[PDB]
Amino acid sequence: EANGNQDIAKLEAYFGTKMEMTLKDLPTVGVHTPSPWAGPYWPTYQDSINVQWSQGQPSAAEKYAKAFGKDVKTFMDAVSKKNGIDSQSGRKKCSSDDDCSTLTDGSSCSIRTGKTSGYCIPTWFGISHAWSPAAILETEPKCPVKHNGVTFQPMDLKALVSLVYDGARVQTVFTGDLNPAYFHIASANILGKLNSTFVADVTAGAEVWNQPVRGFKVYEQTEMTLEEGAQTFYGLEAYPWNAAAKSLVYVKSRLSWIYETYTDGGLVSSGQIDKFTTGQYYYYLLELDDAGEIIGGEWVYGSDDDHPDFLWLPKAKPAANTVTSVGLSYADVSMLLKKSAACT
Image (cartoon, rainbow, N blue to C red; front, side, top):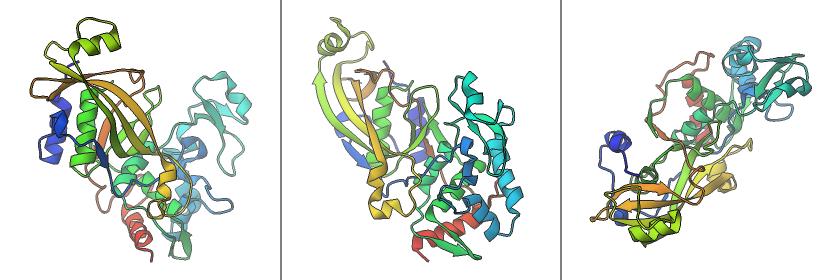
């Protein structure tokens, strides 16, 4: 099926350069360095960043309140009202997980720390859309930082900066079912030619999942005549999906992204980031014209249902002194992030 130049335009505007469209001139491997860092999606059902990810240790929220002179009870309540358990007051009230058995959305009874009853919240609700761009744009916290008597773990800082990105306006280049021609062209140009990366939805199911991409590799390119492709993949004597298509190329490629973890420390500088890098193969026919330029594509081999819904890039970090509606100052968080990365 033919390729829409609408999404390519958005990219060409942002990068200030034309996209490479000739398949033979595209790179077959592109890795983004440094890798985006691993971190959790700070689920809503666990009360966002109010969660004690470390046993016995105060939450990242509580640590932020203590350090920067805010009331713990009210700051954590603010976190919960916007992003945590209290943000779902309208959902079915519960005391145990037995109560939520009526629903069919994947709910789990969610009770705040100190409280006795809560609400039935789906466990996938979170801030993956906020962590992903932070993983890319923000240098990973490496080692602990003490500020006003409280120690912030690299993981605590990952929590704080993630919620900042949720609360702040982050400018995006949003693009996207998704044409495999576009997928290949975007992935090869951004990861390969432009020393950059993006955020992808890798589920293609009901729920939305955001992961920062680490790399893209082409594992196979196999030229095919229109007649060869049509028979092999559709059982047809002629290729129906694009009148303008002159020849075909079967491509098998792998996208590589970072997944969630609560593991503390600077995972990227450790080389430990490899443990939290996963991926998926994608199979597609690319449509070529006479000049060997990609003009379209078709998904094959069950990548028909299982392919990324959209691709987006964060244009830049949030503005220097932004304060979230939860009371989270990006100025305060940036200060701690700089010390964590430089190890002071």
